[PDB]
Image: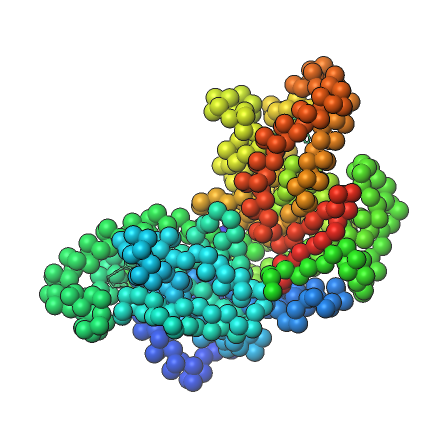
Length: 306
Length: 306
Ligand SMILES: C[C@H](NC(=O)c1c(F)cccc1F)c1nnc(SCCOc2ccc(F)cc2)n1C
Ligand SMILES: C[C@H](NC(=O)c1c(F)cccc1F)c1nnc(SCCOc2ccc(F)cc2)n1C
């Protein structure tokens, strides 16, 4: 007896799902050009249902907002509209957080209840390399203390206060640093998706996850994430690393097998240990845990018992 | 702004709430039967309205349960009813948590959506004095490490899993210790209230508050709380301390002068520090913060914007 319902992949296909509202060819196009780490079978059989499951909660938080406002005789100090519904997305580097976020954003924005869905990466809340150097934490990029937690907290709080205007800084993966001066503006969306390694981590006081209405954790076998991590690394040689402006240009010249070495080293000494100390223990805090099998398809969902 | 809708006492009284919810005289017996200090006007003017708020939340959760269950063609592994709705009640020692919890228990039960409302204090999860001693922690009773946190977590998880049956141990303030083989059974209530000064405290992993659907923080000026503390202590000379078995019998003979000295020393050195370092930091993690005046009246409410 546990606090979630479990479905393996069989049981999930095998359910009398209520709604048609299927994917028009206008949508199924935009969808190939952000996934491809995700196939449309997955979008149809897995992510769409999820999006509706989530739609149910956003819709419920919208009705309750209103039922409450009416109950109070909609007083002056109550805001005029529900505040954004914030969804957190967590998991290891290379697990697919980013795609999953992009897909959900796309699907969730299909309903008229909540057409404005924003997306923000916690990447923009890393200290700039300048500062990471100043605090002697370069070797520590991606661990809890490498982020400006205070600013991140300030940001999410600002969003849940019903600001019409909240700013987050941008991180460039190419340049391996915060793009100075660049800012993402978020103007009271209906839903904000916040993605990052750290979104379900546990501060001493208030923490960002305290302002989440729903949170999702992307899980895989640790060997499999290594495999995905390495493949992503190799691939970056010809793309990202190829650029002369890449902090990691000197990785471009690596032969396949030499790059495989380097990758498994960066994995075994930074990314795997981070996952084990800081990310994987946050798995049981998610509303929903999705497990992906060796080749990226979901083979198990855990929804928190409603 | 803040993430809070804020009302003071005036504003809160002066609201048109378009259901005239009235307490029966059948209910005004029970609510005097919970004791005194208890101001019946405040039950009518504050706690009943709040009870309606919290009700709107429980009703939303029960419907959302159902719409989700429908959506999944009600599968076998989905539970049949909603799991209990959990509400945390935190705040200092002597701030009146226990009353607030007891009144709420009584008012929430009046609706037929959730007539079964259980109340459990986390004092039952303090380590027995015996164990507090093997661990050299008697001086630290009421701080985080004096609780069997693991046990507390299993308890709460069992209730949130939807189990039919869950035990908590019972603590006696009379004997100043856990009563051996005393047990409180909780049998899938519609709502469980969990009162304790630690309920909103952070764990590094999963933590109890992760299972709350709603939570309350009873607040006051720290000087005011001391004064209440000091009376509770004095008054205890007649009641608790007066029995010759009571661990604190010697305290019955302290004159108003020596009794105050003693109370302030226990405050200044145990209860006040536990509050500054462990409880007050938890205050911004509550859905609702209730602030009290010197004279025990509620003078400010902060609800988390919906
Ligand atoms: C430790 C470090 N940090 C990050 O790049 C990082 C991240 F990948 C994600 C979020 C925050 C971060 F600081 C790192 N991880 N891998 C590398 S080298 C390869 C470049 O980045 C990749 C990122 C994801 C991959 F799957 C493969 C490579 N570095 C320099
Ligand atoms: C810190 C400590 N702990 C507790 O007894 C206690 C509690 F009162 C409540 C919950 C958990 C606890 F460990 C304590 N605080 N005051 C005392 S001695 C005086 C008798 O207890 C009182 C309890 C509550 C009061 F408001 C005033 C006095 N002790 C032993």
